[PDB]
Image: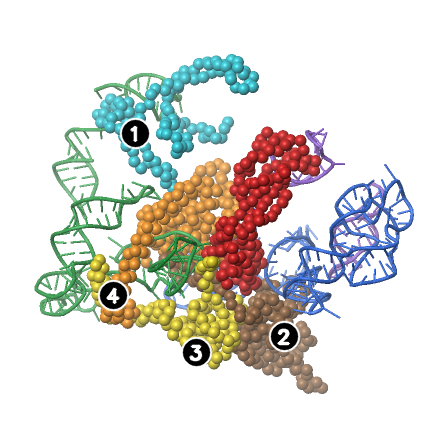
Chain colours: A yellow, B red, C orange, D cyan, E brown, F green, G purple, H blue
Amino acid sequence: DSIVKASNWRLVEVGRVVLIKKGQSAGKLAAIVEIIDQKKVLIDGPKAGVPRQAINLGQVVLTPLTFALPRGARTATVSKKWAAAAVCEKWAASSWAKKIAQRERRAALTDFERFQVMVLRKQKRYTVKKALAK
Amino acid sequence: KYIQTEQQIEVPEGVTVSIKSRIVKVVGPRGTLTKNLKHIDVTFTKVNNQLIKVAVHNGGRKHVAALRTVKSLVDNMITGVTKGYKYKMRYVYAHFPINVNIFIEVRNFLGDKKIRNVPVRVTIEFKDEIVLSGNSVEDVSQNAADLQQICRVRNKDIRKFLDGIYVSHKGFIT
Amino acid sequence: VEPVVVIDGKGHLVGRLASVVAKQLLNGQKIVVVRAEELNISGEFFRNKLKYHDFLRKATAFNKTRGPFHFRAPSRIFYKALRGMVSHKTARGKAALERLKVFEGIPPPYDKKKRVVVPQALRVLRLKPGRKYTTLGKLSTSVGWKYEDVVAKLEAKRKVSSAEYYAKKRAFTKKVASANATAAESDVAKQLAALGY
Amino acid sequence: GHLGFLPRKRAASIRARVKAFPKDDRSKPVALTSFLGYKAGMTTIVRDLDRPGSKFHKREVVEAVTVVDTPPVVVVGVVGYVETPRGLRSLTTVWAEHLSDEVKRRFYKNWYKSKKKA
Amino acid sequence: HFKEYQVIGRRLPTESVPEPKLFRMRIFASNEVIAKSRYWYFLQKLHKVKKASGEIVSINQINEAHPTKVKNFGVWVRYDSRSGTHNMYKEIRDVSRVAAVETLYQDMAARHRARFRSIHILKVAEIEKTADVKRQYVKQFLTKDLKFPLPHRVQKSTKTFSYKRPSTFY
RNA sequence: GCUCCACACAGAUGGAUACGAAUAAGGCGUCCUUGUGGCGUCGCUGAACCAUAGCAGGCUAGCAACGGUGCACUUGGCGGAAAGGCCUUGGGUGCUUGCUGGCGAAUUGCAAUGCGUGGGGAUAAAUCAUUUGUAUACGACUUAGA
RNA sequence: GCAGUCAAGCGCGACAUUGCUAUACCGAAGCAGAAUUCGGUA
RNA sequence: AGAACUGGCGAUGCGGGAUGAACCGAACGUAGAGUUAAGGUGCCGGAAUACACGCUCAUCAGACACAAAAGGUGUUAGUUCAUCUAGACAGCCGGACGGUGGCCAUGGAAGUCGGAAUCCGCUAAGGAGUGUGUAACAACUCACCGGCCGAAUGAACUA
């Protein structure tokens, strides 16, 4: 009987899908191909659209999702492995991508849509309050 | 700079190790020992339920020192829990007999009226020799050191005068 | 953004926190600092203790009282640190300082109100890992502060019954989430989900 | 002289105020700690010293003493103090239903001309 | 951003010496003017040719063959400092020669305090196979199945006040 | 302080929306042998949650809920660190945009946001006067006299 | 100081070297005890 | 101390430099809009708690050329050599001999209180001995090899 708790870290490695935080391809997924050094990692996001390049780890944030990928894979092989792993489907199901989509939708809302949202929220609150205390 | 350096600790079938945030706990036949390592900044893993790894990432020699000493401390704790540690000291006197009563009090040391007392932090048992045993190595060792360091022969020749109590033997209780 | 901002000073750098508080004060923002005794300063304890002595060693000969004043309370130390960052001896500076309040712990009614932190001033976010640091409370106790015991004693009571308040809030949110779930999948809920809500 | 007894300025209050009190005991029963009195006179005292191995052991010794008038003290109320970061604070005070004439006079500077509205 | 340039000079050919040795070398610089100046300085120092009788036959920019291929670069550098000039060799794991030379210049300006003024790039070469690297810090990244975390990430804050007590977990 | 007479009138405009602890770790739900336990789940900023419709927010008729909310009461509890605030039982009185109708907007003309003093009546206290020293150069201080 | 050997380096040049001209508390001493000497805190 | 030639001052305001005679830019009518120099961008102080690579814990650091030649089991990078899967450094175990107790010195000194040479036989390995120690032997030993061990290690220099 042994216990080792709270040791889950998102290791950076080959095949580690990542999300770009800053740069031209900000907000676009990328996959780490080969690690250059402690501060430089090669990434490829052909499915997303970002061209293959060496990016600084400070400009990108890792993600929990992972998939197998041969070291130093080319663009074609990286895209093939990305399609096979279907990491996109897992990404959407995660609450992180859902939060991103919700934020984008809220930023894309209109004044009339905002009024409709307000009315629907009022109705939902009335229904919830009626349900409560019963 | 080292990308990742790890050290291994064995887990005998007779003990169980429960690891959370750096605080470390050990359980075994002789009892349970716990220690705090929140200031050491190391990580632990459960590789196969029988071996415990301590690793440091992007740590230099300064951090590697703590990385390695973590293994030594854990091994010492495991050995103490499984078997324990024993310490002994010898009574030597030329003219004035030394009487010791258990807190441990030393009387009639070099004809000194004052009674030197060393608090007990570890057990006392018995030739003219004391036996100290305890699960924690640090506690028993510090008690022995304090016992040896209270008998200071101030303003006297070190070589000529040998009266006092000194550590003689070390080993496991088993 | 908020008529009054309560900043939790625990685990914060004195320098950055004081600078940001002074800058906000110059902008017309009221700020209240709490848990001053928990404030941290970079460097080992001895260096901070030595630094304190060399600023109070300059006692004026003819008039010590009218000269430098040495305050031991952590709140007083924080105010002195922030005071130098503001253009004092002027009406604009004097007015700004009136918007700042420093207390040890969280005296009421601030104990029942929300508090915030400054990410850029967090000790655990700026200092390099494994580096030595000093605690303002311990330094104040060493240099003469005598209220650390009472401060800790009545701060422990602050956590007491506030854990119970949080437990009650969690129990209420349990029912709130249950009501939201049972109200889900409805036409209004579906429309809200489509509209980003 | 003694820097600890400076500055040498006139005392503001004629009656000396106690700065500290004996440490409280949580096991001993409730008991008093201080008493009030008035100094009155001085005289000589002689006795025999029982101090062991002394120059005057089991033999007479003389010195000077003083006498303080200590009439019985009567309580008038109880004061409670709480622990606060800024120092001990008095939150509530309760006084007795009846008070002595001297106590009432103490709260007056023109007692003869005042209405004695104690 | 550094750039790689090729410069060739043949000292203004005169009678009885047509088409001289035509000294050739590769110069790393941020612009053509700096590349030409560095080429002139190198010719004056190493060789006996000066700009008085010199001539720039042609200057061209060389682009790395595989800008998306990770390589181990071995660089021989001769630089001058407060003490006497001495040779130096270093190994860099980069993607392109330009990036490798830029990192070398940054390291020299950081550690040895040597700047672009007193640094010479003798040769840049690619290490083909493993076990030819002679630097431990470069061998560090050559281990098979290399995985490591990024503890204590320095998250950036866009607002002065944050009601979250952010955690540096990664 | 009580009473009668004469006279004046550094910066709100949604909500400062309450745990603690670690940051080489943490919360939330659930389960069990009740443990530094098992599973799922979340961060990667507050770009968040409540509320936000009505001549600056009126009148009035119905439907469905009987819930939400302002008001003075009313039973009780908590808050001494700067408690002075947090609620909680019962009813009453209004709104309810939760839902469906009928009335007015205009001319403002294309915008210059749109609560003590001074004169009396009575009554609590203080200074001097007076006088004792415990204080004393003079200030100042401790006392006594309906 | 004068005169000679030096020689990591740059005819100059390193460590050695040859002739005159208070109280109190700790560490060491062949501290047997006392007494004493040398170093440190102040 | 006194002279010879040469650029600013002096007759000179402005910005920057905590202030400024030997410092930088800029040499001047009264106004509006815009772009800059030196100098700056955590507050005082108008401007990024910008990016990237490395460095330093300093018990009086640091942000200002003499005392600076050297010292440090402080740290990060380089150069010249030695060992190296014929087994790298390190930690334990074993061997660590015979003439011999070399000659002289002897109150007793046998490698280690002293003086002068340092050999053969060898064996994978013995200095007629690097130390602790006894009035002398006794006992341990490092340097020298072997065995258990498993990859890079060591000596000297430069930043």
Q: Are marks 1 and 3 in contact (CB under 8 Å)?
A: no
Q: Which residue is mark 3?
A: A84
Placement of F75 over or under B4, stated as above or below: above
- C-alpha distance separating marks 3 and 2: 43 Å
Percent coordinates x, y for residue C177 in the rendering: 29, 61
Res C26 seen here: no
Percent coordinates x, y for residue H10 in the rendering: 54, 56
Which chain does the residue under circle 3 lie in? A
Which labelled disc corresponds to residue E123?
2
Do the residues at discs 4 and 3 belong to one chain? Answer: no
Res A25 seen here: yes
Answer left or right for D101 relative to E18.
left
Of the pair B84 and F130, the residue shown nearer to us: B84
Q: Are marks 2 and 1 in contact (CB under 8 Å)?
A: no
Q: Which residue is mark 1?
A: D77
Q: Are marks 4 and 3 in contact (CB under 8 Å)?
A: no
Q: Secondary structure at mark 3?
A: helix
Do the residues at discs 4 and 1 belong to one chain? Answer: no
Q: Of the residues shown, which amino acid type is indicated by label 3?
A: Ala
Answer left or right for F90 relative to G5.
left
Placement of G27 over or under F97, stated as above or below: above
Q: Of the residues shown, which amino acid type is indicated by label 2?
A: Lys
Q: Where is residue C169, by image quadrant?
A: bottom left
Mark 2, Cα crowd under 10 Å, few <14 / some 14-19 / many 20+, is few
Q: Secondary structure at mark 2?
A: strand
Percent coordinates x, y for residue H5 in the rendering: 65, 62
Q: Of the residues shown, which amino acid type is indicated by label 1?
A: Gly
Q: Which residue is mark 4?
A: C183
Q: Secondary structure at mark 1?
A: strand
